[PDB]
Amino acid sequence: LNSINTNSGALIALQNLNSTNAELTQVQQRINTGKKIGSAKDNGAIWATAKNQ
Amino acid sequence: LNSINTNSGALIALQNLNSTNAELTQVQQRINTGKKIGSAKDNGAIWATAKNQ
Image (cartoon, rainbow over all chains, first blue to last red; front, side):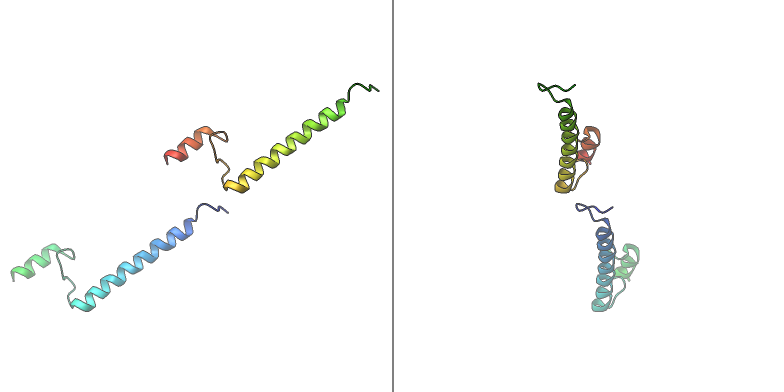
């Protein structure tokens, strides 16, 4: 409380903002590639069955 | 009592003034560093724990 060296609220706010930027990056990928699973990182099993099909 | 060669009241007054000056110096150090434990002299166990942390 009332510290000058530490600001935990800014840390939690930056964590929530980084989560929002991660969701926005996922939506940007969904928009530009047109696929909900555009790579093995999205879902390896469905992407594997898709490459085989 | 009624001595000219000594003044005990000035001695106790100097002791109280030195205590007040030490408290003001501690408050100045806390205003400076921003830490209530800025060094090992303040509290060595908690200080070493914070250093490892």
